[PDB]
Length: 22
Length: 85
Image (cartoon, rainbow over all chains, first blue to last red; front, side, top):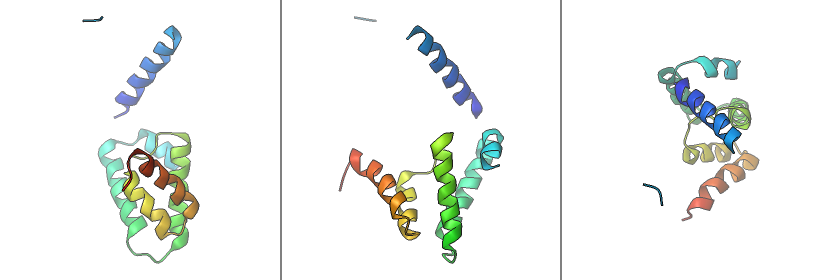
């Protein structure tokens, strides 16, 4: 499926812009 | 053409392509040039876009069988470095 590749690509490209815990 | 078909075509059929291609690269060991061509294919695919999900363990021995020692060193080191025996 290309959904995994596309979704990971969007998440990566949008985390690149932005560049204890419970 | 291989890249342009592979990017669109579906998973249950690309796995058929892989299982056909591995038998092509393994059995009926008459042609060395066809083996060289398909190793160059997987080289190009892994070089640019979405490498084919074949296991490196079975990928390694094909280079030795085709006497592609240059390929063999590279795809053997990646297996060695994580764990040796």
